[PDB]
Image (cartoon, coloured by chain):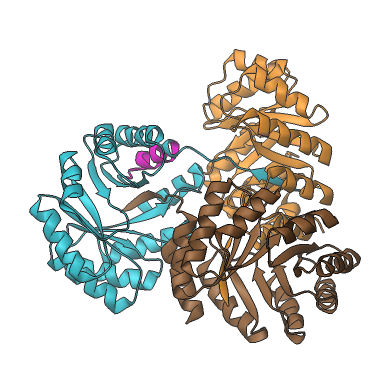
Chain colours: A cyan, B orange, C brown
Amino acid sequence: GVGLHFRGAEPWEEKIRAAAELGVTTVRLDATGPIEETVARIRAAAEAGITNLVLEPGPLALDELKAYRDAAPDTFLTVHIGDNPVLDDATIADIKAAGADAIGIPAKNIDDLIANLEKAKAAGLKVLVGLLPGPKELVEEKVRAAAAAGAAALLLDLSDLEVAKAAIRVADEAGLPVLAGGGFDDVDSFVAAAEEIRALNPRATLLLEARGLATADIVAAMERALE
Amino acid sequence: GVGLHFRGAEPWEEKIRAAAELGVTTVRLDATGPIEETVARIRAAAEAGITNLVLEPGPLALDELKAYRDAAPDTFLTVHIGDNPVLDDATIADIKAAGADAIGIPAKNIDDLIANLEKAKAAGLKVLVGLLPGPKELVEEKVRAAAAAGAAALLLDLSDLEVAKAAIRVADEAGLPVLAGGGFDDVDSFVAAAEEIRALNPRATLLLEARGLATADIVAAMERALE
Amino acid sequence: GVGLHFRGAEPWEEKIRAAAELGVTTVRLDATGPIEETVARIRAAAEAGITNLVLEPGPLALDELKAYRDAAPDTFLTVHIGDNPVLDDATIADIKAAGADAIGIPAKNIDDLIANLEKAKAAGLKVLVGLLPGPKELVEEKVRAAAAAGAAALLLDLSDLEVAKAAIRVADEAGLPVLAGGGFDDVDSFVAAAEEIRALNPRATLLLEARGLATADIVAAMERALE
């Protein structure tokens, strides 16, 4: 016997609560959709025990920023700016004015990485530096540059696992926390890599892409990695 | 030469009709979306020859229930209640009043499984008992409990294939039909597992997750398993 | 450390521009959605340097056709008719009247393939013939029929890679360009198959399914295949 299953798109709140009960504390959240559902998700994360929250919104007015901050006032809120490496002193103030605990800045080259780190740290913001996939030697140099120029944490979207291990190992040398993702929608591949990352860098968190997985499979993935 | 393909989301009706022509008779349908498209899908399933239909709606008023029943009056309609293991005698009547041939009940523990089976069977409803993924010994005990307490069929959302084979083998011992799914979006992995499930339990149906696959690939998957 | 990532759906324009900068020139675009976002995507493809554009719309009025043609007047626009193998002389005129450089026609059997090729070529349209997955010998005969009856190019939606290689090799014998896809959402499997297709047929383009992949991973996929 063979049949068809048309599985429904599960609410993100259910997935957030299921993971947090197992002990998950970090969620990287896309905040480009409508405000009402984004705020609702953040509130559920706050109730579930999510202590580290990384928003990735699109255009972000100060109204949106305060709404997100108020949706989880006791969490470590990090606002990711997106794509454009330009960092005007105005948008820094808005993220600062809303109570964000940190700002997320992409790293295309190192010269703008140093300038952005100077701008945001001078304005009292902790900085989470993100690296785009690239050659292994270049990524290592950017990890060192981010570390030396005062980054609080590293965001690694490196689907090349071997390159990612290299960057994570360099970050561990500097005692840099790492948020790692990329190419992890399979359950079995994730739990294997979650054991490897832990050995390379104890301060490193691996992110499961949870948008398309069933809640039960997320629980299975988190159970096998945490335990 | 390399290029980009932005494939469009295909209507579920096309996929239902394509599978039914090959001989597929069981469809597990998410019924959380708008009523008009859900009813339209059910009607196409009725025209295509779908004889076993498992709805998984969200909130479900009696108006929705009768609409679904009338969309395919000659099919074996099973209404799945969702998540909350509480089973009030009122929602049982509504599913009964609408002409549903069976009700779908989750099994978190065995004590509420026995109580829910008593409640629904006393009210003349056939019961399809669903099992969440868990330890192999626990799943087997729940299969035995469901079988002994009068379940008409088992729903297995077990992504751990080896555990799923264990539950399916225990169900075969009791002559229990099984609807099985979980982690089957790949074509090649599905057809392999479809041959294994058949040997373990002739009364067992394996469900292909069809939400993201092309219609041609669904036809290829069903052709290789049925033949 | 383990966490959740809820990645946002990235605009198709970003993916189109990222690929075109690497040198990609062919995009197969679903044109069933609203006109405004479809036209916006086509314009971005025109600006990015996409010279071969294959639209796959649903119902298509002449208003839609001219809008798409005007969104990229310097590109080789191919309009794919969809599913129904019937080819009335009226819809041929509308595609012709809008300035389309070619028409896409499915091939269920060979007799309607010959008739449709006669109809569209007599009306001055270049024809891109698409083949549905099937037995290896049948596909080869259809490639020969399409080639002998005057097809300008072949569209291959063959998830069975070995069958696809057979059709591509037969097309190379006749000097037929090929657009190939099917089952390519994984990065590593795509780049491997992109090297094999090139050897079999230099005039053959392999399409990456880009709807669900991150822009960075698309860049990684295109970099490894082009170089």
Q: In the figure, residue A6 lies in which quadrant?
A: top right
Asked if residue B68 is positioned above or below residue A216 in the image, the reply reads above
Quadrant the N terminus of chain C occupies: bottom left
Q: Residue at x 11, y 55 (%)?
A: A121
Report the side of A10 relative to B173 (left or right). left
Identify which residue, B65 or C179, lies in the foreground. Answer: C179
Q: How many marks?
A: 0
Residue numbers of the magenta segment: A14-24
**Relative to residue C36, is residue C182 drawn left or right?**
right
Taking depth in this image into account, of A87 and A168 the one nearest to the observer is: A87
Q: Main secondary structure of the magenta part?
A: helix
Q: Position of residue B146 (x, y in %)?
A: 64, 32
Which residue is located at x 35 percent, y 65 percent?
Answer: A196
Query: In front: A44, or A172?
Result: A44
Q: Is residue C30 visible?
A: no
Residue A8: horizontal and vertical position, in percent? 57, 40
Image quarter of residue B227: bottom right
Q: Is residue B102 above or below residue C222?
A: above
Residue at screen point 53% across, 49% down: C37
Say whether residue B61 is visible. Answer: yes
Is A19 a magenta residue?
yes
* Residue at far front of view: C97
Q: Position of residue C50 (x, y in %)?
A: 53, 69
Q: Position of residue C216 (x, y in %)?
A: 41, 65
Q: Residue at 58% across / 31% down in the picture?
A: B106
